[PDB]
Image (cartoon, rainbow, N blue to C red; front, side, top):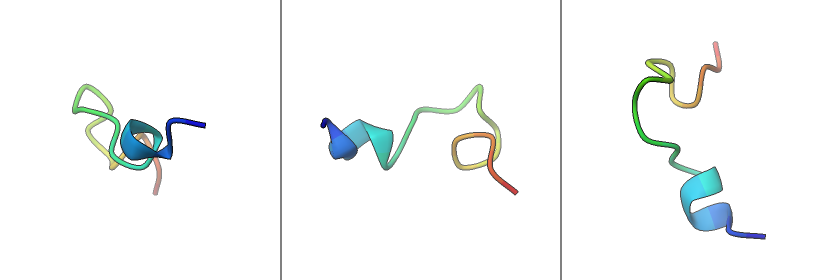
Length: 20
């Protein structure tokens, strides 16, 4: 889908999308 952003979710994820 929109990998775009789904590949770079803005902060407030403070973990590159809440990842490791």
